[PDB]
Image (cartoon, grey):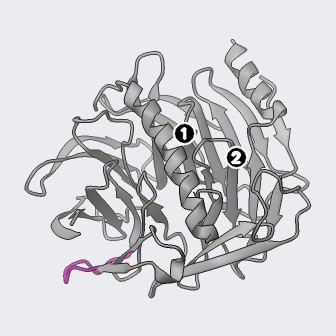
């Protein structure tokens, strides 16, 4: 269950990273 | 996944690293860079499995052997940047549009085996070297923020390192069979980073890690990645081990530097991948784990399970792909998986 519970932290933290990414407008290569 | 295309770079030298640019905004073309020998090449993925050449860089130093690369951007202009490094022991920051080296960093006493950019601050670059140390650089002010090594640092080449999702700490591993934790959200490290921005420099010397263990693998540890608060690391025993510092119930941020326990939660077994410097990768959402082997086979595990032993493993193969796959990379949207080999070949797999 530890491995399953860890997945919650992943979901929450990747969401945070995705939100910061959504704010950016990095110029394409 | 389905195999849709493959090509071989004309220099025919082994390719060691590959990275999609995860900074590109939604809708922009999926681009990735490959590195090996004194070459750095950029490609753009298009429909019908097309892999378009975008730009290329050939170092004047013909003896350089790039081992890895990492993407970031210039925060002053929102322009993408690519850091590369390898056997020469020099970090080069290349402008991917003009393919010109704009900055370089020297300090490591030897080859650099891995580069990683902070997940929040684009200016913070972490390098790990054959010289037994890790170094943190601020590429905006061109300063060495800190050196991780010394009294309790690694005692042999550092082969890999990874920041956790939020960028609060680092886990490193290498030839001394150990895995070490270095927190960077400490008052000391936060302050060092802050002062590095003020420079127009005295770096912090971090000699003591916040955790260290040699009880996971019995040989060199050539790749480590954070999986939430858990750790994924591999040696040469054809298995990626999932473990955590402390006991089953211990919280990663509550463990003391002297903690002597570890808890192994399971492993992902595979075969024919016992040569050194074969790296595994995960997609941005960390729902998939991938690793290529020495004979061209690409293993892909579904991480959305309750335990590693129940993770479905898909073996991707193509009768013409028989070279060692050094590294793979998923596009940010997990729609494409690229693999690079020792024979300079590149393989594209589009999501199923």
Position of B312 relative to B352 (above/below): below
Quadrant containing the N terminus of chain B in the rendered view: bottom left
Residue drawn at (83%, 31%), measured in percent from left and top? B187
Q: From the viewer's perspective, tell me whether residue B244 is left or right of residue B90.
A: right
Q: Nearer the viewer, residue B171 or B243?
A: B243
Label 1 sits on residue:
B119
What residue do we see at 59% from left, 69% from top? Answer: A3
In-front residue for pair A2/B256 = A2
Identity of the residue drawn at 22% across and 39% down: B29
Please state the chain letter of the residue tagged with numbered disc 2 in the rendered image.
B
Residue B54, picture quadrant: top left
Above or below B281: residue B101: above
Crowding at dot 2, Cα within 10 Å, few <14 / some 14-19 / many 20+, comes out as some
Q: Is residue B66 left or right of residue B234?
A: left
Q: Which residues are magenta?
A: B316-324
Relative side of B321 to B167, left or right: left
Residue B296 visible in rendering: no
Q: Earlier in the sequence, mark 2 or mark 1?
A: 1
Q: What residue is disc 2 on?
A: B169
How far apart marks 2 and 1 lie (CA) works out to: 11 Å
Indicate the position of residue B12 as horizontal and vertical percent values.
29, 64
Q: Secondary structure at mark 2?
A: strand
Q: Quadrant of the C terminus of chain B?
A: bottom left
Look at the image and say whether residue B320 sits in the magenta stretch. Answer: yes
Q: Position of residue B61 (x, y in %)?
A: 45, 45
Q: Nearer the viewer, residue B27 or B149?
A: B27
Give the secondary structure at mark 1: loop
Per the picture, the main secondary structure of the magenta-coloured stretch is: loop
Q: Residue at x 71, y 32 (%)?
A: B144
């Amino acid at each position: 269950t530890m491995f399953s519970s860890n997945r919650q932290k992943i979901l929450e933290r990747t969401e945070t990273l995705n939100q910061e990414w959504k704010q950016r407008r990095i110029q394409p290569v | 996944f389905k195999c849709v295309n493959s090509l071989k770079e004309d220099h025919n030298q082994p390719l060691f690293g590959v990275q999609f640019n995860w900074h590109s905004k939604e809708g922009d073309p999926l681009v990735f860079a490959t590195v090996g020998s004194n070459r750095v090449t950029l490609y753009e993925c298009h429909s019908q499995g097309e892999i378009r050449l975008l730009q290329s860089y050939v170092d004047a130093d013909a003896d350089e052997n790039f081992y890895t690369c990492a993407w970031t951007y210039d925060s002053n202009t929102s322009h993408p940047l690519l850091a590369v490094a390898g056997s020469r022991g020099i970090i080069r920051i290349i402008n991917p549009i003009t393919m010109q080296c704009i900055k370089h960093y020297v300090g490591h006493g030897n080859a650099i085996n891995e580069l990683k950019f902070h997940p929040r601050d684009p200016n913070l670059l972490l390098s790990v070297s054959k010289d037994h140390a890790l170094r943190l650089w601020n590429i905006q002010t061109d300063t060495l923020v800190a050196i991780f090594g010394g009294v309790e640092g690694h005692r042999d080449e550092v082969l890999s390192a990874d920041y956790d999702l939020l960028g609060e700490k680092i886990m490193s591993c290498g030839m001394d069979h150990s895995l070490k934790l270095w927190r960077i959200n400490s008052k000391r490290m936060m302050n060092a980073i802050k002062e590095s921005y003020d420079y127009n420099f005295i770096s912090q010397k971090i000699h003591f890690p916040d955790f260290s263990t040699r009880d996971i693998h019995r040989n060199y540890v050539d790749c480590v990645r954070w999986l939430g608060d858990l750790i994924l690391s591999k040696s040469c025993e054809n298995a990626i081990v999932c473990w955590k510092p402390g006991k089953m119930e211990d919280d990663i941020d509550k463990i003391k530097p002297s903690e002597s326990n570890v808890t192994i939660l399971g492993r992902f077994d595979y075969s024919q991948c016992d040569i050194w410097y074969m790296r595994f990768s995960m997609d941005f959402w960390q729902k998939m784990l991938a690793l290529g082997n020495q004979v061209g086979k690409l293993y892909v595990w579904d991480l959305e399970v309750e335990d590693p032993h129940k993770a479905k493993c898909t073996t991707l193969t193509h009768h013409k792909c028989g070279a060692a796959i050094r590294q793979t990379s998923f596009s940010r949207d997990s729609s494409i998986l690229i693999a690079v080999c020792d024979d300079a070949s590149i393989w594209r797999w589009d999501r199923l």
